[PDB]
């Protein structure tokens, strides 16, 4: 089939890894995942191509609703009919549903075109002009992001009446073409020899190994004897662990750490004891070690792919039985765990359990209580499942068998509890499966909010075919926006050798279930290719020639045939709803930063004002910390809007796309507090006192009565950023990374340093809040009010921040690698305290930042 071979080269191109590389591994796990996932994904591709037209809209154009709408006023809208210049502007209510708007559009059409139309309002969908956005469903118009956004900017919604027939034309054009428990002996292994080893000649090499279940030690850590340093060290010694073979859990991992002493770590390596087919491993294995920066229980259970350089470690997994031993089936595990003894205790110990389970480290006598009252947990306190799972002796199969009996009979938990079970603290595969079962309830909007964390959990996975992968693939194929971001979250880390096989495999499976989207993602990947080359010309040229000259040699290069085709007509990788239509070459430029970031301007004739967008292409810098912080800010925005608090936040797009490569979304009509404070002459803001510049600037951008709105936009946005930077630890705040929109909105940029590494408020910010006045405690205290209100809202969702940041440890961020970094967040959200005790601390911290604010005023 010539059809398949072209698809095959395109997939290889898109994932920046040849599909021949996978078949060159000779690996059956890789081949079984490929075959099984292609099956699963083509079944999804088939389901989708036969979806209803409204159902196909829900896949392609999932609704962008306001946080308040999820789970009154007079409005003016302009409606057109697909394939016509003629448009109708009309009045509607913010309480009207799209069906009433479509009935208005058809009634106007009927009188204008002089026809008693057969055309039903139910037969249409409202597209947002020049955007991959639709308004459908029975929701009042204000509930839609585009409408609600339009009201705030004072713009007119621009819609196109799209008939069910053209939506089916879209679907059709986009279709895919045609026994262990009987082996009492302790755990032992023969450490044979090392290969391609590097260490100082003075030193004497030792191998240390431990048996783990995620983090927790199954038994005491055991080290080996000292060997003289050479390229090929030779041990041939037996390490006997304090654990019977029957007591080994399913998810047991044997972890190694090679370190030279007279003290320095050289390399580390891990392997699962049971294979993907649940059989206990025996024989000789070649552990291609990763460079060490004291075992690494978290690191990949897959060897270093660069088999040349890597310092290998030859081991012998000894034969435990003269027959192959597999891990007992769930039906076997449940038999052993069913027959248990129930905990009967007095009213006194009943108080102790309710006290401790609600109150998360414990004491060894209390762990014995929680285990004895484990039936009471399932019944009275199900959400305490995590505590109980932690007090389970995972190195003893009888206890583990008793736990899975309660787990398989456990009620489904809320999404907060399930997200907590995704952590590496709960490495059991049935616990992983239970957590996912309790997450199936996630809305596509919620899933999209936690997608980044779920992607990091993929790195904690021990085997390729897992329930999390199956889930994120099925949700991606059921939603084109989830599909888009899942693709990019994976594609961006393809340069990392530990994840390039897993991520490359997930992308291939996705591509098999979405042939059309692949071609849409290839077009994006082709634009990004050209931007790297164009950035490289800029980087070189900016050194030799002045900025106006480089700017024009870039503009010349952009005008080239291949660049014009490449950079035009594409879905924005920062937003699939945003179409990057016509590149405005003359308006493109670059920054005077070390990486010479490129500013790419775009416009749409069909979208009008909505099409005038820009992207920033940054190569040389790692954007993963900006994307986290912004996603965390966006969360706060959603959390606040849900309590009816709109703090006019600007959580702009930021997306890593490759190795120190990514895009950031341009927020137009905005300057830096720095550029404004320059206080340049002949400018409208030219201030007598520097404190005035910022307000003179707002006065200049918002004439007359509008300034009062611009001050409120600034006050609210200012309050939300004071909290965001406190709670999050956003340090290194200068005048050049605090920006202001012409609307009055304040926002922060350049989040390379968070979590410590209180609030930063100068008197010109206080001056704007105070409306120029010196003494204005009425206005200043509303700002403190908004700050406290916003902070109390976040604390209530403190655990959601805690659990998200926890799963984000897997991401390999240097400022987010251990529990000492989640510490800042527990301190800032004051979670081990009652709301008043927490408010008292916030008040003190606010006053302490306010006393630090009056240092500026002293002058
Ligand atoms: C620091 N420059 S960057 O890499 O382009 C970058 C940009 C942004 N955002 C994205 C949101 O929308 C924006 C709008 C404006 C700006 C900006 O820096 N304009 C200044 C204003 C004063 N002029 C004299 C020079 C240009 C930046 C952003 C964020 N992060 C970045 O890096 C980490």
Image: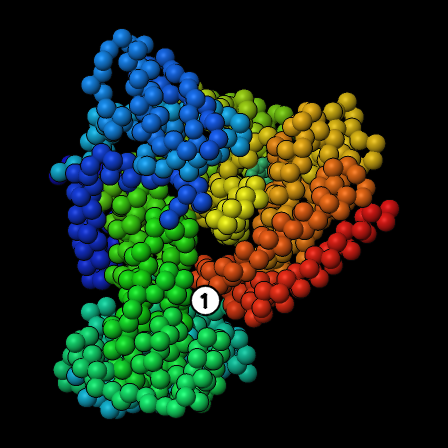
**Count of numbered tags:** 1
Residue 688 in the image: state x and y as whole percent.
83, 32
Residue 549 in the image: state x and y as whole percent.
61, 25
Q: Is residue 44 among what the camera can see?
A: yes
In this view of the protein, which residue sits in the foreground, 162 or 777?
777
Judge from the rendering whether residue 830 lies leftward or rightward of residue 390; answer left or right.
right
The residue located at (77%, 55%) in the rendering is: 852
Judge from the rendering whether residue 94 lies leftward or rightward of residue 100; answer left or right.
right
Circle 1 Cα neighbour tier, 10 Å, few/some/many (<14 / 14–19 / ≥20): few
Note whether 768 is above or below 239 in the view shown: above
Note whether 660 is above or below 795 in the view shown: above
In this view of the protein, which residue sits in the foreground, 213 or 685?
685
Which quadrant of the figure has residue 759?
bottom right
Q: Is residue 540 among what the camera can see?
A: no
Residue 552 in the image: state x and y as whole percent.
57, 23
In this view of the protein, which residue sits in the foreground, 153 or 232?
153
Disc 1 on helix, strand or loop? strand
Which quadrant of the figure has residue 3?
top left
Q: Which residue position is annotated with label 1?
A: 291
Q: Quadrant of the N terminus?
A: top left
In this view of the protein, which residue sits in the foreground, 531 or 297?
297
The residue located at (44%, 35%) in the rendering is: 142
- Please state the quadrant of the image where ligand 1 appears: top right
Residue 146 in the image: state x and y as whole percent.
44, 33
């Amino acid at each position: 089939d010539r059809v398949k071979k072209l698809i095959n080269s395109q997939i290889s191109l898109l994932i920046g890894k040849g599909l021949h590389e996978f078949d060159s591994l000779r690996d059956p796990e890789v081949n079984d995942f490929r075959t099984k996932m292609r099956q699963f994904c083509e079944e999804a591709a088939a389901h989708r191509q036969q979806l209803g037209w409204v159902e196909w809209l829900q896949y392609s154009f999932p609704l962008q609703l306001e946080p308040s709408a999820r789970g009154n006023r007079a409005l003016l809208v302009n409606v057109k009919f697909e394939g016509s210049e003629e448009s109708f502007t009309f009045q509607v209510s913010t309480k009207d549903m799209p069906l009433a708007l479509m009935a208005c559009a058809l009634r106007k059409k009927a009188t204008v075109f002089r026809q008693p139309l057969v055309e039903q309002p139910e037969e249409y969908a409202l597209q947002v002009n020049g955007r991959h956005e639709y308004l459908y469903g029975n929701y009042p118009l204000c509930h839609f992001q585009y409408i609600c956004s339009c009201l705030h900017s004072g713009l007119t919604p621009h819609l196109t009446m799209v008939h069910s027939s053209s939506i089916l034309a879209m679907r059709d054009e986009q279709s895919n073409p045609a026994s262990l428990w009987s082996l009492e002996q302790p755990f032992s292994i023969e450490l044979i020899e090392g290969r391609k080893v590097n260490a100082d000649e003075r030193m004497k090499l030792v191998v240390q190994a431990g048996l783990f279940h995620g983090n927790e030690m199954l038994c005491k850590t055991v080290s080996s004897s000292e060997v003289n340093v050479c390229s090929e060290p030779v041990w041939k010694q037996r390490l006997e662990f304090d654990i019977s073979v029957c007591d080994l859990p399913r998810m047991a991992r044997l972890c190694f750490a090679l370190y030279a002493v007279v003290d320095c770590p050289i390399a580390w390596a891990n392997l699962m004891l049971f294979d993907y087919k649940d059989q206990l491993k025996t024989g000789e294995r070649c552990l291609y070690m990763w460079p060490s920066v004291l075992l690494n229980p978290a690191g990949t259970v897959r060897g270093n792919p660069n088999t040349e350089s890597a310092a290998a470690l030859v081991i012998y997994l000894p034969e435990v039985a003269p027959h192959p031993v597999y891990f007992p089936a769930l039906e076997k595990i449940l038999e052993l765990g069913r027959h248990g003894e129930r905990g009967r205790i007095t009213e006194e110990e009943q108080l102790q359990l309710r006290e401790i389970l609600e109150r998360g480290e414990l004491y060894e006598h209390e762990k014995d209580l929680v285990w004895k009252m484990r039936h009471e947990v399932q019944e009275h306190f199900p959400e305490a499942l995590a505590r109980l799972l932690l007090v389970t002796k995972w190195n003893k199969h009888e206890d583990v068998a008793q736990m899975l009996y309660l787990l398989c009979s456990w009620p489904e938990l809320p999404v907060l509890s399930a997200l907590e079970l995704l952590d590496f603290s709960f490495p059991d595969c049935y616990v992983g499966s239970f957590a996912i079962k309790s997450l199936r309830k996630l809305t596509d909007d919620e899933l999209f909010q936690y997608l980044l964390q779920l992607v990091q959990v993929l790195k904690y996975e021990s085997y390729l075919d897992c329930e999390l992968t199956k889930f994120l693939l099925g949700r991606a194929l059921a939603n084109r926006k989830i599909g888009h971001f899942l693709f990019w979250h994976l594609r961006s880390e393809m340069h990392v050798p530990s994840v390039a096989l897993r991520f490359g495999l997930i992308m291939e499976a996705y591509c098999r279930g979405s042939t059309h989207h692949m071609k849409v993602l290839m077009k994006q990947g082709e634009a990004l290719s050209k931007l790297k080359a164009l950035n490289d010309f800029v980087k070189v040229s900016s050194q030799k020639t002045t900025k106006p000259q480089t700017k024009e040699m870039m503009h010349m290069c952009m005008r080239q045939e291949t660049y014009m085709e490449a950079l035009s007509h594409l879905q924005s990788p920062l937003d699939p709803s945003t179409l990057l239509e016509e590149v405005c070459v003359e308006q493109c430029t670059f920054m005077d930063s070390k990486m010479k970031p490129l500013w790419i301007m775009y416009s749409s004739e069909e979208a009008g004002s909505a099409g005038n967008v820009g992207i920033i292409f940054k190569n040389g810098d790692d954007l993963r910390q900006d994307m986290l912080t912004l996603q965390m800010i966006q969360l706060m925005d959603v959390l606040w809007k849900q309590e009816g608090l709109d703090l006019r936040m600007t959580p702009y797009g930021c997306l890593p796309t490759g190795d120190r490569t990514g895009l950031i979304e341009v927020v137009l009509h905005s300057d830096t507090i720095a550029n404004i404070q320059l206080n340049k002459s002949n400018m409208a803001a030219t201030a007598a006192f520097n404190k005035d510049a910022l307000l003179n600037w707002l006065k200049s951008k918002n004439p007359g009565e509008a300034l009062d709105r611009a001050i409120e936009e600034f006050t609210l946005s200012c309050a939300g950023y004071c909290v965001a930077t406190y709670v999050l630890g956003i340090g290194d705040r200068h005048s050049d990374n605090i920006m202001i929109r012409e609307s009055g909105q304040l926002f922060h940029i350049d989040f390379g340093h968070f979590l410590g590494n209180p609030f930063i408020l100068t008197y010109d910010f206080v001056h704007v809040i105070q409306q120029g006045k010196t003494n204005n405690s009425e206005k200043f205290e509303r700002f403190r009010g908004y700050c406290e209100r916003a902070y109390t809202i976040l604390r209530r969702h403190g655990l959601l921040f805690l659990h998200l940041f926890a799963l984000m440890r897997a991401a390999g961020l240097p400022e987010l690698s251990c529990s000492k970094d989640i510490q800042y967040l527990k301190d800032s959200l004051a979670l081990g305290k009652t709301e008043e005790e927490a408010l008292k601390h916030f008040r003190v911290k606010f006053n302490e930042a306010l006393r630090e604010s009056w240092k500026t005023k002293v002058n």
